[PDB]
Amino acid sequence: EDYLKCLYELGTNKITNKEIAQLMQVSPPAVTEMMKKLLAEELLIKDKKAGYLLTDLGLKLVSDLYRKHRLIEVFLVHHLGYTTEEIHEEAEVLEHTVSDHFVERLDQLLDYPKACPHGGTIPAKGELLVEKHKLTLEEAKEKGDYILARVHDNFDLLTYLERNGLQVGKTIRFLGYDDFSHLYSLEVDGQEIQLAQPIAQQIYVEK
Amino acid sequence: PNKEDYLKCLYELGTHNKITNKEIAQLMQVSPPAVTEMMKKLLAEELLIKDKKAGYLLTDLGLKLVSDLYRKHRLIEVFLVHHLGYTTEEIHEEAEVLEHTVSDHFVERLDQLLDYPKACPHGGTIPAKGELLVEKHKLTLEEAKEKGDYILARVHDNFDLLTYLERNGLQVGKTIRFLGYDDFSHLYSLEVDGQEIQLAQPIAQQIYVEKI
C-alpha cells in the first residue's frame, strides 16, 4: 500500500525485487512479501518487458493519492502561504489524516484547480492520472525558447531549482546538450547554467 | 486520554467546586490509579498546583496551554464550517483528529486566512496567540434571574447537547423567550419559533444567554 506510489513514478523501465531494496527502505526478502499479496489483491501484474505493471484497480487507487496530495499543496501554498520547505514538513502528515470528504470540499472551495502549484495534474475523483506536461528536457531536442512547465514533485530538486532560479512557469532558452559532458546548457535570466542528466529528466518544458 | 484532555476537563470542571480524584476518573472514564498517575505528571510539569478549597488550581502555564487547545479547536471549527460547509455531525467525526495533528504554523496561518475570527460558530471566543481565554458570554440560563426575552449567545461543544438543541430548534443567535424557572418543577420553560419547550436544569446549565 506504501510501495505502489513508487511503482508508478518509475514508469518514466525495468523493475526487479531489488529496486525495492535501496530505494524505499525495506530489505529485498522483507518486501517480496509485498507482491505476493498485491497479485492476489489484483493491484499489479508481472510483465517481463517492463518488470511490473499496475492494473487499472492499482492506477486508480494511486491516482487518488496524487489528487489528495496536489489539492493539499494548492491550499497550503496558495492560501496559507507556505514555502516549499514548509510543505516538506507538514504536507504529508495531514495528507495522510484528512478524509475524502475533506478533499472533496477542499476541491470545491478552491474552485476545482486543474494543476498543482508546480506543474502536476489534478485528476478528478475515480479517474486516471494523465499528466498534461510530459515533455522532459532530456527529450526536447530542439534548441531555442521554451518554458519550464512542470517539475517533478521532489524536495531537493526543488531546493536545488529555486537555488538555481528555475521557477515552474518562467521562460527558458535551451542552449544545448554536450555529447561527452552530459550537460545541458540553459539560458535563464540572462545567465547560463549547466544541469546534469538526472536533473534534466525530471523537468518538463514546452516551446 | 492525554494530558491535554485532562487539563481541558479540569479547566471547565472548575467553573467552582472542589475537584476530586473521583470526578476525574468518572468524567474521563479511567482507572483511579490511572488518575493518580496523570495528576503526578500535571504537578511535575507545573501545569497546576494542589489546593485545599478548589481541589487543584491552574498555573499560568496550564492556563496558557488551555488557551491554545481552544484556539486550535475553535479555528478548526470555523474553517470546516464557514469554508467547507461541514455539518454538526461531520465535525463530530473529523474535527478532532485534525486537531491532534496540525502544526501551530498551520493554525497561525489558518487564522490570517479566516481574518482573525473572535468567535467559533457556537459563541465561544477565540483568544489571541498567548492570551488567556476570557469567554465573552458567561451568563448561563440557570443564573438568569429576570424573565422575558434573550439572545441565545453560546452553547457547549458537546455533541449530544448539540443534537438536542437542533432536534428542538434551539440555535445560537436565535432569540429566546424565558418563561421562568419553576421552583419545584425544576424546569426552565422557553418559547422559541412559536413552540414551548421544557428544559431540565443540567441542559439549562450549558446554554448561555444575554439579556436582550
Image (cartoon, coloured by chain):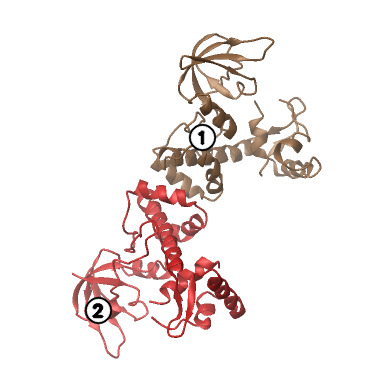
Chain colours: A brown, B red
Classify residue A7 by image quadrant. Answer: top right
Q: Is residue A132 visible?
A: no
Q: Amino acid at mark 1?
A: Pro
Q: Is residue B105 visible?
A: yes
Nearer-the-camera pick, A163 or B156: A163
What residue would you read off at disc 2?
B144
Q: Amino acid at mark 2?
A: Ala
Nearer-the-camera pick, A160 or A153: A160
Task: Tell me: residue B50, above or below residue B120.
Answer: below
Q: Position of residue A169 (x, y in %)?
A: 46, 24
Residue found at x 54% / y 78%: B25
Task: Tell me: residue A146, above or below residue A94.
Answer: above
Using residue A25 as the reference point, say whether residue B88 is left or right of it.
left
Front tag of 1 and 2: 2
Mark 2 falls on what kind of element?
A: loop
Task: Tell me: residue B125, above or below residue B52.
Answer: above
Q: Position of residue B120 (x, y in %)?
A: 35, 59
What residue would you read off at disc 1?
A123
Mark 1 falls on what kind of element?
A: loop
Nearer-the-camera pick, A115 or B191: A115
Which label is found at residue B49?
Answer: none
Residue found at x 63% / y 35%: A56
C-alpha separation, residue under disc 1 versus residue under disc 2: 56 Å
Give the letter of the chain under mark 1.
Answer: A
Task: Tell me: residue A9, above or below residue B95.
Answer: above
